[PDB]
RNA sequence: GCCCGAAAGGGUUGACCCUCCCCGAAGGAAACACGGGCGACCGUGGAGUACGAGGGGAGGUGACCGGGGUUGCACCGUCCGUCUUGGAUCACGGGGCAGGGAGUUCACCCGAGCGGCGAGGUUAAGGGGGUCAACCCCGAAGCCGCAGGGAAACCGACAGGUCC
RNA sequence: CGGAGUAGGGGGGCGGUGUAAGCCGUCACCCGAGAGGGGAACAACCCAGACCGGGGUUAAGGCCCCAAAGUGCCGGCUAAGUGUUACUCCAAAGGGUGUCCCUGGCCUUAGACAGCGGCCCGUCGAGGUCAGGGGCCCCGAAAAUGGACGGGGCUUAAGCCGGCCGCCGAGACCCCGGCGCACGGACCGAUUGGUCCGUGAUCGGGUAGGCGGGCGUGCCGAUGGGGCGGAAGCCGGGCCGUGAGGUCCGGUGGACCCGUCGGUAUUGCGGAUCCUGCC
RNA sequence: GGUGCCCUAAGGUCGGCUCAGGCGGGUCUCCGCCGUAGAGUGCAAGGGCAAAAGCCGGCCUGACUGGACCCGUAACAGAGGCGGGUCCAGCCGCGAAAGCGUGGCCUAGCGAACCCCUGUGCCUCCCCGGUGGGGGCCAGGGAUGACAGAAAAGCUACCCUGGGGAUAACAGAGUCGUCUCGGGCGAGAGCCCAUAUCGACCCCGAGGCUUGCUACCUCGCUGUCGGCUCUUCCCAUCCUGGCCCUGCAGCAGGGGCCAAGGGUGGGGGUGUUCACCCAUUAAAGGGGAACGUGAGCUGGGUUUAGACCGUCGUGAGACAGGU
RNA sequence: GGUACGGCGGCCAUAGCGGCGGGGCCACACCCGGUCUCGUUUCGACCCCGGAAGUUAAGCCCGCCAGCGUUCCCGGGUGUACUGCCCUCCGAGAGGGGGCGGGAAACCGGGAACGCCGCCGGCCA
């Protein structure tokens, strides 16, 4: 399954290995989102930076909306139904249905950027940046409930 | 009070032998064979005091590059420097 | 708010202000109508509407605008240089103005940015000529380089054989 | 291959020693060499890393007045102004039918107090009694100029416990325009280069220090110009310029001055308990 | 806790054999048995070691010569001198052979330049060639313990300079072992009676008025003790007001609660603060304010320059000893 | 093809200590003696030399046993103790707590376990 990861906290006051892990994962700034494949190698890194991000499983509909609004190409040009219907023989909903299940990867679309830069959340984060999401805060594994947050940040 | 390094400094457990070995090792080790490019572990047998390198490098892994006498030449990486040792094969062990 | 405002800045080929329309990023209501919750409130619709930085255009009014001096109101703000882990310091230097005031020159050595000749390169002291401290021609003595090893005696090498 | 600077470190976490303060190390996150938003104010505790002009949403945390936004909703506790303190900066052993709760035994249609008399009847007839565990508060609890929850003040709170719902709030994040930088490309140049195009979520803080380009001052060799129809200098002003600074207007003044190219230098001051002169 | 050495064997090899301790016999070294090492190893500690690396013997002198490379001191990451290790060649030892042997089972027992001594065999000394004597290459040795290496005693109170709060005495900050003031529990004492009074041994604290520890501020700000003068504050209350318990008859005493409005003085010796003493008194409390107060006084003490005594010192001289 | 035989080995206690029942043409042992090969600070007791009169009692070989020691598995102890990262969590403080990840030792009960694997023979047919 595909995983969505959002960064929330800063690296000042953080160890030197967490910053390097985050750079590898392409999470350089706050309110920045990355999509990733569920594998042990990636689970290790998420376990290391569990205290500066949130993550979960993403959905077809949410990835379609994400692509339409916050998806950019090289040059920070938007993504369009024509661009996709041309470079690939399908539209954006189908593209996303595939990505979230296999049969295709995001990089199969040329000049796509692997980073979605989001807007801060409306109504704000409704919890503490200092606790986990299960004990009443903002961080850690949230499952199918990362989609609500993405839609708020979109 | 400072204290220089020397061969047998802080070797009370590293160069101690389990109470159930206590003697000669089996003879499938003095007559080990190795090839070039073969990776080896540096593991010291405390009963044999010939060809024993500095315990500083106990537990490290190197590559064989040659042979001189009954000894083998071994290269290890220490930071960014290369270090070359002449070791008897009872102190060595093949990978996998 | 009061005061100056000629020129060098804009402006009667129209200043300031006024209203009208079109496009409109990120974002983004309310009244009101139905229902959920003990409740603060929320959901669907209204509605991505009304609005929105800015970009364009159409008109009315007819002389200031920008700039400067001082001052009122609200918010913000413990000077300057210096060593020191650490300066608003009860640590040192600090009454005001104007002028002066601190990485230079030689000789050897290591390197570079350019330029000339090139298995050779380069002249010194000096000499001759001239329109006479500028200019022109001669002058290789010597120094570096082309063969190194060795305390010394002494001996004395690949102008290309193979591979990546 | 060349040019440095550094040989007093400190907050915070871990270890040895020490009554402790502190001493000696270690870790490499921060101050030093780091702005901005909050903690009343605070070097290193929280959010967060900063070209310029503007628009909007958030973080830390906050929402009775000071002070932007709730005299917010539900359930319960405290009567001591306890408290109104994340940390920086805050008292114990020992005790309490103060109150609110959990648990387990023994009693009960006559129990546990009273009263009337010799273990008892009736008598007023309904809930008692013993232990153990927890929450909040109380005693224990005494200082020196005049007072500190930041202050006013607050008692079904404007306090504490358990949960919830909406707003306010940074230079953070999103958007719009402009500047520069690094990399690559084209064209173009009498010489260190210039004009444009692409990319930049992965460029834009800086002490010691290293590198690049420019402003200004005096003299030379050349080139091109101005001046008694008023040069330099001085005063007050306008415009360009990130800036070092340049240039014009008016006045005063009464003879010299600037630009471009290349060279050269007693070449730029707020400080030295600096020197001279004046006040 | 140890080394600044010892060893011709305690060094090389070959062969044979097993230890300390105890049990059971025999008397005051003999037989058997159990015995993973509880012994020994040239010397500390740690590690290693049983047909042995221990003990008993036999033969030898690899404790040698000429030379390479690598590890440590000194991690990562620079190195002179020293030390160790793996090898090539030569000559040899032990052993039937394979094999081992470049000192001591491993880790301590030592040292640059210049100069000198010894050994060995060759090169050289100013036109040439001889003799005597000089210089050089190679190897070994003589020492610097402050041991990566100067040839080397003290006073300053007549003192000077340059600097330091990187560093003391003095007041501040921090801390509170010590200090002052308290508490819990109940052993025991009080004719009997745990609590009138005393309260051990053990446990828990406040304050910052003693003293220490540290070294954060200040090295030309001022450096100070006591006294006189003058103002103010705390309460942990000495008297003065009001109360409670008593092993409170009264007069009184002891112990405790509220209370800080007022008062708490004069003199003797001593530089004194405190402490001691006298006579009175309602009683003659303890502390803070930069150990309050020198741009307010004084100037007895203490820390300059003069001099005396005692001790110490060869002496110059010193004494937190006196005058 | 057969063996109640043997030599050289590897893993080096799941193999070890102790205890028991059985077996012996060929082979290993215990045995008789030793002059010479060899030697016992003194003895063919030890070691070396030549044979077998005797037997399986010992060593060797086959089989078993869980008294001691070792090793592995199943449940508990127990997700206990300790621990890496984060926290505007508690507490006067000492020290504790929550979330995400790893995770024992003793002890208890129950099993298995009294060795596995190579190369070469010799003899019976």
Image (spheres, coloured by chain):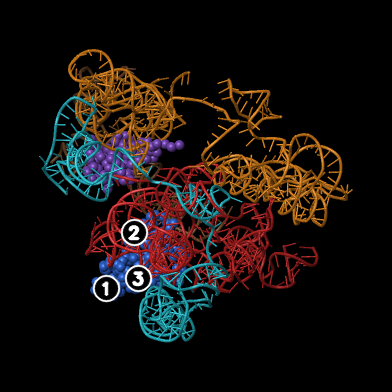
Chain colours: A blue, B purple, C cyan, D red, E orange, F brown
Q: Residue A123 in the image: state x and y as whole percent.
A: 45, 71
Compare marks 2 and 1 and give the one earlier in the sequence: 2
The residue singled out by tag 3 in the image is: A70
Same chain for mark 1 and mark 3? The answer is yes
Q: Residues within 10 Å of mark 1 (few under 14, many from 20)?
A: few
Q: Do the residues at pointers 3 and 2 share their chain?
A: yes
Depth order, front residue of D94/A53: A53
Instruction: Please state if E317 lies on the left or on the right of E40 as rendered.
Output: right
Can residue A107 be spotted in the picture?
Answer: yes
Q: Residues within 10 Å of mark 3 (few under 14, many from 20)?
A: some
Q: Which residue is mark 1?
A: A83
Against A141, is E2 above or below? above
Give the structural element (helix, strand or loop) at label 1: helix
Residue at screen point 43% across, 37% down: B2
Residue that badge 2 annotates: A24
Real-space Cα distance between discs 3 and 2? Answer: 22 Å
Q: Residue at x 36, y 36 (%)?
A: B7
Circle 3: element type: helix
């Amino acid at each position: 399954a595909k995983l969505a990861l959002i960064r929330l906290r800063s690296g000042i006051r953080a160890r030197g290995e967490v910053r390097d892990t985050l750079a590898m994962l392409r999470l350089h700034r706050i309110n920045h989102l990355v999509i990733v494949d569920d594998t042990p190698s990636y689970r290790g890194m998420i376990q290391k930076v569990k205290d500066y991000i949130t993550w979960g499983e993403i959905d077809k509909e949410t990835l379609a909306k994400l692509l339409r609004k916050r998806g950019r190409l090289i040059g920070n040009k938007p993504i369009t139904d024509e661009y996709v219907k041309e470079k690939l023989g399908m539209t954006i909903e189908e593209f996303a249905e595939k990505v979230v299940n296999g049969e295709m990867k995001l990089r199969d679309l040329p000049n796509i950027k692997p980073v979605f830069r989001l807007h801060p959340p409306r109504g704000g984060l409704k919890g503490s940046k200092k606790r986990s999401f299960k004990e009443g805060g903002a961080l850690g594994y949230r499952g199918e409930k990362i989609n609500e947050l993405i839609e708020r940040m979109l | 009070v400072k204290k220089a390094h020397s061969f047998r400094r802080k070797t009370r457990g590293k160069l101690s032998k389990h109470p159930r070995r206590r003697g000669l090792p089996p003879l499938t080790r003095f007559l080990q064979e190795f090839e070039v490019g073969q990776k080896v572990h540096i593991v010291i047998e405390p009963s044999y005091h010939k060809g024993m390198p500095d315990p500083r490098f106990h537990g490290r892994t190197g590559t064989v590059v040659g042979k001189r006498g009954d000894a083998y030449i071994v290269q290890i990486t220490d930071g960014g420097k290369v270090k070359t040792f002449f070791i008897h094969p009872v102190h060595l062990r093949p990978q996998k």
